[PDB]
Amino acid sequence: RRRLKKVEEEENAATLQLGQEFQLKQINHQGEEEELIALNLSEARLVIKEALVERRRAFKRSETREKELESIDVLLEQTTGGNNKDLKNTMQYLTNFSRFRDQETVGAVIQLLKSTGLHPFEVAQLGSLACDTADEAKTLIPSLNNKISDDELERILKELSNLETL
Amino acid sequence: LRFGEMERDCMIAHGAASFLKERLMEASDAFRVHICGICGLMTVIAKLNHNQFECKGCDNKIDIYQIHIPYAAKLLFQELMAMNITPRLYTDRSRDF
Amino acid sequence: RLVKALEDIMVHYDNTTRNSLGNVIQFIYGEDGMDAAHIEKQSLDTIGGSDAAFEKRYRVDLLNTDHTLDPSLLESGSEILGDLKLQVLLDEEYKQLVKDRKFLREVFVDGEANWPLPVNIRRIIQNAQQTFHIDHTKPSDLTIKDIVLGVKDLQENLLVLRGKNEIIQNAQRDAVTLFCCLLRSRLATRRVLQEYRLTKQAFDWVLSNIEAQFLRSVVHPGEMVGVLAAQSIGEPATQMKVTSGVPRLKEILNVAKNMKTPSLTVY
Amino acid sequence: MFFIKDLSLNITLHPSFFGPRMKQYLKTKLLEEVEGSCTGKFGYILCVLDYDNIDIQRGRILPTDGSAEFNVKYRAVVFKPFKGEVVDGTVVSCSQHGFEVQVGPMKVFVTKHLMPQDLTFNAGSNPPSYQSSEDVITIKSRIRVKIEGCISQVSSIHAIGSIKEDYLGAI
Amino acid sequence: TXPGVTXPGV
Amino acid sequence: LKEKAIPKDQRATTPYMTKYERARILGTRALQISMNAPVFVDLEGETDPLRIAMKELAEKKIPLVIRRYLPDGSFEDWSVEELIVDL
Amino acid sequence: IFVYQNNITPSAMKLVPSIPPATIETFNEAALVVNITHHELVPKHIRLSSDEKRELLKRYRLKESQLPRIQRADPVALYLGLKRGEVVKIIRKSETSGRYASYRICM
Amino acid sequence: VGQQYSSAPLRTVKEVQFGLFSPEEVRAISVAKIRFPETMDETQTRAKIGGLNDPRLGSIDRNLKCQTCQEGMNECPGHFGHIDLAKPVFHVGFIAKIKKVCECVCMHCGKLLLDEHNELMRQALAIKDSKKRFAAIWTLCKTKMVCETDVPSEDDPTQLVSRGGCGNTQPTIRKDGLKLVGSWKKDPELRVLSTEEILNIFKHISVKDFTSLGFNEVFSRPEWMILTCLPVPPPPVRPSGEDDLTFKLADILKANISLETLEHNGAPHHAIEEAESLLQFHVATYMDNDIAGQPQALQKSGRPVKSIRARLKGKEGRIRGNLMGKRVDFSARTVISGDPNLELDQVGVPKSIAKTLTYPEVVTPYNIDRLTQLVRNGPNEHPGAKYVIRDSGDRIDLRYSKRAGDIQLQYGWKVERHIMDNDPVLFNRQPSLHKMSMMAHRVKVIPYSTFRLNLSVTSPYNADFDGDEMNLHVPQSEETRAELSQLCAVPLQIVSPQSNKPCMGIVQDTLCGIRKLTLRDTFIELDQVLNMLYWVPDWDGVI
Amino acid sequence: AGRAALYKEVYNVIASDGSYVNYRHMALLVDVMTTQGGLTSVTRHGFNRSNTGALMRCSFEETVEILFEAGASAELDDCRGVSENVILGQMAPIGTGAFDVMIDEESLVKYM
DNA sequence: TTGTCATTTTGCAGGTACTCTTATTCAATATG
RNA sequence: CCUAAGAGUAC
DNA sequence: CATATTTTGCAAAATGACAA
Ligand SMILES: [Mg+2]
Ligand SMILES: [Zn+2]
Ligand SMILES: [Zn+2]
Ligand SMILES: [Zn+2]
């Protein structure tokens, strides 16, 4: 309720104190509740590209890193206008640190991490970070301690590293 | 001229709500005052030219609203505050009808 | 004081009368849902008169001669006699009229016939008679089944509450029962065919206007009936053995344990 | 990290703007106002999803004013930095107090206090960089950094990061 | 009474 | 708000426009016309915004809806087009 | 129902509430000489069942407190043995319409 | 020019949540600590820093901006200060409530006396509304005068269950003026309950205990009924010849300083108690000067001081005198006269009144020409315009602007022009006991100094022409104009809902004439028949 | 029966001098006076002692005491009454204000 | 182990608008 | 300018 | 010589016993 000025804890991924508006369940615009899904770098980049191409098509009706950057710049200029410096920086950051290429690989990754039955924040971090070993991932992400077996995390990171291309 | 209580009652009986609001606000005294969503008090420092709104105590700067109330209403609320009463004004419902 | 007490009473879109807290004061405004400005004093014909006068006014028999109808009144006056279904219709209509007579005599113990009701049927009948030039000599084009079914459909069409459940339907019937009694009292088969001598188009026009005027007389949601009632009581007070007038009004509003003239009536 | 969230914005339209292209005006005015914006409640707001049919609803006329208040609901992609989160980035500048790393749309300033003692600033090289015993961190160099604090700023945000933990630095 | 002319009582 | 909105197929309010509804529609439309809102009807030379709104209402060319609020907070949406102006 | 002549000792009034669901109602014979329900001022009272009360609250979108109240000491409520929360339908011969139905919740 | 643009979102107040200031909230919202009773410094030309008119609370001079918000007196709401009281004092409006609360709570351990173990406490606590709960709890716990550290078991009155009681004996508390005196049962010992100890015992009441007493955990805790920090209202509340509130606040500061010095330098308990009583009296009379029994705090001129409660209550108080009803602009009042030649819904308006009262018409392509013509005519002749409101908020007075030349109107601007014929205007006669005594008429501008109205409309107004005055209000927007013409118009009021019959009729000369005209003896020759037929405006033209 | 007797008393008062008032006004008055289960008087100790909102209740009588009790009890006023909106200077939910006027984009496009 | 009955104190507010005129703002003793 | 008082107009 | 301070309408709530 109002609660006047209520105190709150400081956010920390170690404790997973993301926030009152970053809870696991969020009420969607349709009125029902959906799990808080988080996008990894490649998945977020694909989502951005899909949104931009859809916007470009709606306006119209009404791979290598260099060519990808040229295409995204041209499409950004054609679709939207100005004041997109933050968007341009995010887009180039995503293209530079692009862990995956197309829909098939990101879909396989997301379904694999869904099969892990783990927290969306943790699986998104695992998909984004390109870790190598298991203890390295555990020390990088404190939230993964005492949640999954060491061998299972190691092997799933092995498949993720195998799926890495370019 | 005095638009007394029972003139307001006659206008209510006529059902003309907007005319009553215009009589009580635009014709007499309309005051724009700023409040915050944390505490309903009017203790919001609003530097309009610099575009800076800040309620000290609540320590918020991004949760400010402006409302149009009669200056007599603002004076009544400030007098209640001076008399150790908090007439907190909120812009959303916390309870269902 | 009266205005402040009733200032927040309003008619809502479900026809209930509620205050600012949503408490139900009346489940329908004025117990009939009608705007006060659309109410006129009219006479209920069934409640008064004698039993013989009531039969002569309303009873119609197609198989006897004591209460038969003149065949010249309507076009098919020589074919209706000897019918069975039409006699059943007249039987149920007269039974309903008798039930209405008993009901009205129950409601008004003094037998007062003139009461304020929404739609003025008499003016509608006069307007139809003057508009369609009723010659009062030509046999009527109407059929009895037409009259009965038209009255029934008109009763079905007088809607005050638009809900679609048993509670709301019962409330609607309770709301329109008295006006339906008046309507059956006026648009009876004998009275239509003999006293007024409607035609088919004139009867349809009368039904349409009754329905339109009844729908137009329903109170509008959002009406501030509380302030209206407070003013309608207070203003006549300014024009003003047992205490009366302003002192009695003050004793009533200020509910006082001890009053000047406590009197009791024994029958 | 990047998320997608359900957001709502109130837009007031003048009476003069209720032509047949009102939907177009509302869609355009939602953009240029929230696209690429920044706030402390949701971090950065980068783009809007499902632009084909954004929920505009009906729109309420303000009494005595005539303007209409639409509560447009939409899906927005956001980037909210969080405490104790490891993220990749690129160094863009270095200074005496520390160095700035480009993470998405934000610049995280890692101070010289949050690095191992082997790494030291060096202004001799052009451009000045950070050089250690085993590796050197220069401009346009990939580096992984763990964010442990965030500072809300005007139309921007300057978080606090570190590389002191194991397996933090250039890849 | 009233007041005027509390209650009674109070 | 989805729970509040009574579905159109089972609205139980009067299909006739109330006097207050008509007054507010005429006032709102006149105020909008006074502020150069587009006109959806042809003008026969009339210049008063109120009578322009009256002409718009006469032939149901007002693109507004009434959100009738029930005492419990639920509401029904009635387009001006489908409301019957009998008064 | 206990029907007494003059009065009940208050030492017995305190033990009137027995173990539920058994309820004890006390009436004075002087108060029961004339049946109040036959008075023309007293309209018809019908107790509602739980399903009927639920339907009444559902159809009118009402809460418990928004209904008109009837005290749990009213002579008609004592006559019918109303318990708190139970709703009586009141049938009345109105003069604007023939029949009017009200509802009162016991408090 | 009004108020300039603000980027903050515009909403309407949906809920008003009441409560009490916590002292820490007062200290947080206050912008200055008031310490010096003086309002102006020794130079007598500027506001003293730290005085009662601190510039941080708002500017007392139109020439200077507020030191806090850097806004003029038009915009600045005024920002509160705070006075840190030397010792806690009772709030004069809560003393009775404080007595009830301390009579419901143990005066030593600070726990509610009758817990749920008592039979009647389940009934008391089951009550929903806070006020009824508190009434029941008080009327059952006022008679208990022992903390009852051990109580009979709820299951059976055989074994004893120990609760968190201390076993002390609660005193009987009365009020003697502005203080509470407690008499403990003699093992009576009478002593004045210090406000400090009552505050301490209030701060020890558990959350569950005082939430059953009606108090709120977030908005009103019982210990907040004791004043430790006084919120000082800004100068807008007490504009200057200082206001009564300023003098009372100066007295409060003087008493506070006296008590603080006495405590700091050491003094006999009698002097300390006297200073404390003086401070309590000053605070109480500042908030309420109409305390029964206690003498009124007189002003320097020997009259009672107008306290805040005096400002709020009464017919002329804030609520009834400035909020429920208030003086309004765009209103006229003058003597009324009858006119048989006016229509039922018409009202005759003197030309001077029509030249004074104005309506703002938005400049539109449909009315650019006539509005421009009215602007050209100016305010000195009727019809004409008095002001031109620009889209930027700047206002052009038609007087003194004829030198600048002709003004080019632009769409969206407003022309504030004289009310013309057929303008809907609300028309009233007071007291105005019913809605028909306040109706919408159409203006007809006439060349004499009285309002003119039809004879048939005098009955709903209860108006004669023996000196009656009537009031005229002009709507200032299209919405108000339209709803006034479509809801309050005179023809729509002919049939009153008061008695479902017409409220206007034929009266006075017309009634006598209509009786004399319709007699069987009355015959009219051709010439008079033609004149009478022509006098009927809608006569079809056939004899 | 008390409500019926109250209506009869008020009707007798009104019609003692021959004046006539429609039934529904007196019916509304006597229903308000008896809606709480007892005879609620039109006085400070009657209708003004409900939970109908502090701002509404203070506008009649005992203003400052009502405000003090509201502050101590932390009453929440939902501003559903006329007096609350009159004090706050906003359109009351009465008459023309008993509903919200909104814009249909689809109908507006459908016109042209 | 429970009713009884019989004196002494408990709070107050008065309709709606509107016009005009008149007086008065602590006096005086006391210290800087 | 405020306050108080008095006289008065229409109810 | 000038500013500062000394007519009206009651039902209860509360009280003092109390009685075995
Ligand atoms: Mg007169
Ligand atoms: Zn705040
Ligand atoms: Zn300021
Ligand atoms: Zn204790």
Image: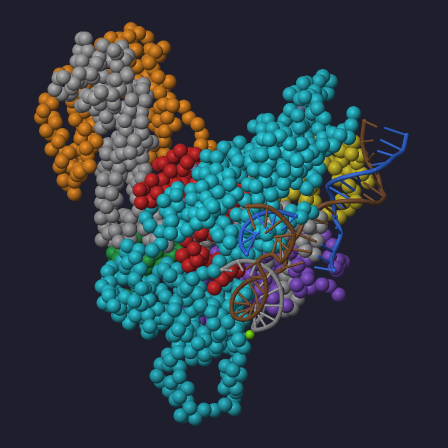
Chain colours: A orange, B red, C purple, F green, G yellow, H cyan, J brown, L blue
Quadrant of the rendering where the C terminus of chain H is positioned: bottom left
Give residue L3's position: percent from left, percent from top: 54, 50
Using the image as rendered, state which of residue C12 and residue A43 is in the foreground. A43
Residue B84 found in image quarter: top right
Q: How many marks?
A: 0
- Front residue (pair H48, H62): H48
Q: Is residue H1 at least partly visible in the picture? A: yes
Q: Quadrant of residue A75?
A: top left
Quadrant of image for the N terminus of chain H:
bottom left
* Residue at 53%, 35% in the rendered image: H84
Q: Position of residue D69 (x, y in %)?
A: 33, 46
Q: Nearer the viewer, residue C111 or D127?
A: D127
Quadrant for ligand 3? top left
Q: Quadrant of residue H116?
A: top right
Task: Kindly tell me whether residue G64 is visible in this rendering.
Answer: no
In the picture, measured across the screen, residue I1 lies left or right of residue A85, that is: right
Image point (67%, 64%), residue name: C245
In the image, is C168 to the left or to the right of G106? left
Q: Is residue G12 above or below residue H59?
A: above
- Residue that appears at 52% across and 34% down: H23
**Image spot of residue D162 (x, y percent):** 27, 17
Residue H75 position (above or below residue B6): above
In percent of width and height, residue H350 lies at 41, 74
- Give me the residue at 73% from left, 47% from top: G35
C257 sits left or right of F76 in the view: right
Residue I80, placed above or below residue D84 = below
